[PDB]
Image (tube, rainbow, N blue to C red):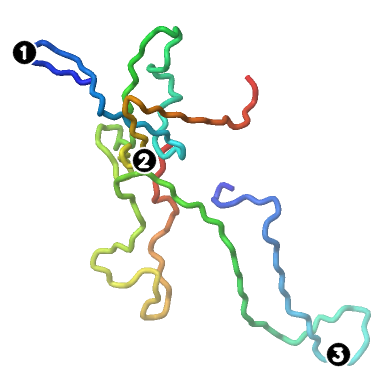
Amino acid sequence: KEVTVQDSTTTIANNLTSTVQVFTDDDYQLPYVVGNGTEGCLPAFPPQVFTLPQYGYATLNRDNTENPTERSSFFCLEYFPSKMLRTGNNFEFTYNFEEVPFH
Amino acid sequence: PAMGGFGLKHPPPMMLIKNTPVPGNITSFSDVPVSSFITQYSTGQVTVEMEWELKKENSKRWNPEIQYTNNYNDPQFVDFAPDSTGEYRSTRPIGTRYLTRPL
């Protein structure tokens, strides 16, 4: 959807030719922020509609201050390959869990 | 192990070498063992061949990393080389960790 404002009107319209980009981090190259008890998971009640969380990370900091170190790292998401989708298109993924003990 | 390295149940084995006793002139019989021997020493060459398995880096870090380099200001000698008398010089200790990975 495209949002336009003229003189405070705020009209909203469909854009047919616009794309969305999707990828999975299979080799664990990126920092993994999923297992730290944070908000933004799919909702408990099926009818509820949800906003996706924004991705971010912390690298190294120098002497307990806001400044970086030479070891500190920058990662670009656009460096990885991604699927491009228009309104007609769909994406699918499959995973197998490793052997683990029963709870 | 605390010093560092690989802990092995079955380590590469102990290799032992000795010079065989060669006796000095004996002209009479005794039950008591001989204590007189000719003085001797040995010399030779030894070769050791070792095979190592390597694990490759698979990093997605955009920015440049830290590396070990030969870097000296106004040097009066070359490090890791012989001097004018022929004695080897090794000024710096070298570790293995220069590459970086996310947790």
Q: Are marks 1 and 3 on the same chain?
A: no
Give left or right: position of B72 versus A7.
Answer: right
Tag 2 subunit: A
Chain of the residue displaying label 1:
A
Amino acid type shown at disc 3:
Ile
| Amino acid type of the residue that numbered disc 2 sits on in the rendered structure | Pro
Which residue is at a point 33% across and 16% down the rendered structure image? A51
Q: CA distance from mark 1 to mark 3?
A: 124 Å
At 37% from the left edge and 35% from the top edge, which residue is drawn?
A83
Q: Secondary structure at mark 2?
A: loop
Discs 2/3, front: 2
Q: CA distance from mark 1 to mark 2?
A: 41 Å
The percent position of residue A49, horizontal first and vertical second, equals 36, 11
Same chain assignment for discs 2 and 3: no
Where residue B43 appears, as percent x and y from the top left, is 64, 82
Expressed as whole percent of the image width and height from the top left, the position of residue B80 reads 40, 69
- What chain letter is assigned to the residue under label 3? B
Residue kind at label 1, given as amino acid type: Asp
Q: Which residue is mark 3?
A: B26
Which residue in the protein does label 1 denote? A7
Report whether A102 appears left or right of A32.
right
Q: Residues within 10 Å of mark 1 (few under 14, many from 20)?
A: few
- From the viewer's perspective, tell me whether residue B79 is left or right of residue A103: left
Check disc 3 and report its element: helix, strand or loop: loop
In this rendering, is residue B78 above or below B29? above
Q: Quadrant of residue A2?
A: top left
Q: Residues within 10 Å of mark 3 (few under 14, many from 20)?
A: few
Name the residue carrying label 2: A81
Q: Which corner quadrant holds the C terminus of chain B?
A: top left
